[PDB]
Structures are given as C-alpha cells and as structure tokens.
Image: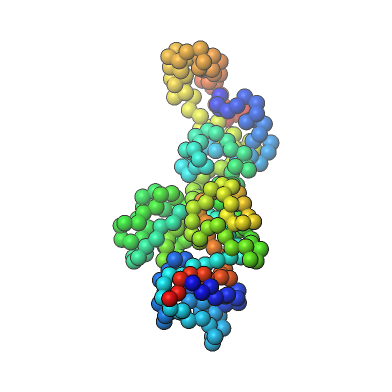
Amino acid sequence: LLDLSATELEQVLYFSKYIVLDPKGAILNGVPVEKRQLLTDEEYRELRYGKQETYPLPPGVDALVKDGEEVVKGQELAPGVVSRLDGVALYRFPRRVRVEYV
Amino acid sequence: PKDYRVQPHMNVVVPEGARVEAGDKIVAAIDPEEEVIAEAEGVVHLHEPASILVVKARVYPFEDDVEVSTGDRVAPGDVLADGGKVKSDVYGRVEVDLVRNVVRVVESYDIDARMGAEAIQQLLKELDLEALEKELLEEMKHPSRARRAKARKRLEVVRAFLDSGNRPEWM
C-alpha cells in the first residue's frame, strides 16, 4: 500500500531512528528531493551539516586552496588533510603573507 | 614578495587577493605598536591557515545594499543583496558577512521528518485510496509485464480497504 521496499526499507525505519521522507523537501544530496524515499538517518544528519567540518592543520603546512574556494568530496584541501565533503573552502587564521611588494 | 611572519596573537583584517599600497596596515595586531604597515604596493595573500573548513553554503559577493538579514530561508531566486543583481540558488540560513563583503547561504530546508511507527501512521492517513486506484488502474494496463505484476497485487489491496469501511490508518 505505502509503496516502500517490501522488507528492507520497512525494517530500516520501523524500529530504528531512520528518518522517513514524508511531505516537503526540495534541497538535495545530488538528486531531487525524494517523494517517498526514506534515506537512513546517516544520510539525514549529513544533509544539514553535510559540508560543515573543521579540518585542523599542523604548523608549516600551507594549503592547496586560497580561502573561499569550491572543493570536491575527497579533494585534498591541504598537503596533510583530505576533505570528506564538497562545497566551498574557507580559511581560519593567518600565519604567513607571501605576495609581491615593490 | 616579502612574506612577513604574522604571529597568531596578531589579528589580520585582510581578504585574500585584496589591494594594498604603502599606507594601509595589513596585519593589524590586537596589540598596537610594531604592527606591520603596508609594505610597498600590490595585492595580498594568506598562507598556512590553522583550519581549512568547508561549508555547504554558496558564495554571493556584493558591493552595496544589504536587504536580506541573517537566518532566513531564501528561495532560489529571492534577491539577497546588490539591489537586484544578487539572488539565492538554494534555501537555508543566510549569514551576512560585512567583513569579507559577501552574503552566503547554507543549503537547508524545513523538511518534515519522522521515525518509528508514528512516522508511518501519518503517511497512511495521507494515502488517498482514491487517486491511487486510478493511477494503478492505468499502471496495470498501459505498462508491460514489468509494472503489470506490480499494480496487479498492488491495486487489490487498496481496493480491499475501500470496500471495507476501514481506513489504513487503523493498521
């Protein structure tokens, strides 16, 4: 009746804390909002913060990205850090300022 | 290009790829005195941040006019800044950043979301026995053997609930 996978998708959200995607939604994760599809809670929580992670850097390890700059899921943000999500990149604090000064 | 080692206990109010000439302080330390001045002319860069963090926002710069405040779900097209030349492409919280002169918006929405059996129950109540009957009444015939077997066993169920007097919500 409720067009879900006869077994898997049922048990998945029937007992567990797995969020069903009933009414609303438009924002995606690579594909248009799911009308009746019930992404697991993993996929749920990774929708709000689904790009909001601080990646600390050791001292003396510059970067591979200059401040505000689009990153890929797995794109090496730094020479020692591999990001785990897409979106844009950002900086934190400045320890070096190398640039042309006549 | 003189690097100038800025110690972390010194603030820096300079955006990446900014414009500075021999009179504009760059690393404006929290502490006054000795703080670096503009060394000659040219652009400005930033190296070795303590944290490179990504965000699910999108970048929308502006030169003037800030009409969209902070914390509101702006629909893909709703004018953010610059009078009418800057619009959003996704909903979610707008964090205006007057410091970098750019208004961004994190990708979020008021998606209705539930768990357990209370999750299913509402989706059962919401199920219109009627529309589905027609939809499957066509999905049974017009499609081939692929969807036929689907609508086959499917339609019978709702058909049963109809001629019974019991809404599926009682399940």
Spot occupied by residue A67 in the image (x, y as percentages of width and height): 50, 61
Q: Considering only vertical position in the picture, is B171 above or below B159?
A: below
Q: Residue B161: tell me if it is visible.
A: yes
Please tell me which residue lies in front, A95 or B142. Answer: A95
Locate residue A37 relative to residue B117 in the image: left or right: left
Locate residue B112 relative to residue A12 in the image: left or right: left
Please tell me which residue lies in front, B122 or B6. Answer: B6
Which of the colour schemes (rainbow, by chain, secondary structure, one colour) is used? rainbow
Query: Would you identify the image quadrant in which residue A16 lies?
Result: top right
Residue at x 49%, y 48% (from the top left corner): B109
Spot occupied by residue A92 in the image (x, y as percentages of width and height): 56, 65
Q: Quadrant of the C terminus of chain A?
A: bottom left
Please tell me which residue lies in front, A20 or B95. Answer: B95
Spot occupied by residue A14 in the image (x, y as percentages of width and height): 66, 34
Residue placed furthest toward the right? A15
Spot occupied by residue A75 in the image (x, y as percentages of width and height): 57, 49
Residue placed furthest toward the left? B84
Q: Residue B93: tell me if it is visible.
A: no
Q: Considering only vertical position in the picture, is A37 above or below B144?
A: below
